Image 1 (cartoon, each protein chain N blue to C red):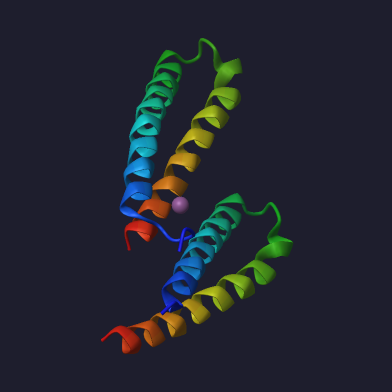
Image 2 (image 1 turned 90 degrees about the vertical axis):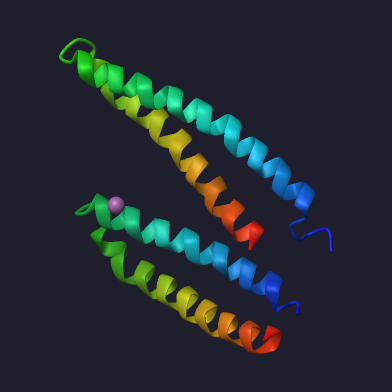
Length: 71
Length: 61
Ligand code: NI
């Protein structure tokens, strides 16, 4: 049935995961660079960490979904 | 079949409750009041997933 994952669906999710892995890498590096520059811009820590967290959380969900889909 | 979709669904629920309990733990003492209800739900889902997987595996053998 349409509900169940297909090779086509898996290929698409793989594609989404790869674009997001790049974006996640960007936030990782930006957070790293923030920490390395401390104390400058310490007021930006929580915001930057939240943004970074959200992208990695989404990435982790999709990766776990992909594994389950592939099956 | 199609136990497989049913196992897939529990697999996902199990993964989410794992995340939820992990986060709740790391966040302590915040929401310590929610520990037992979350553990009970997580246990129920993993138990049911365990059994259903065993069933699918007798099936498919
Ligand atoms: Ni942890």
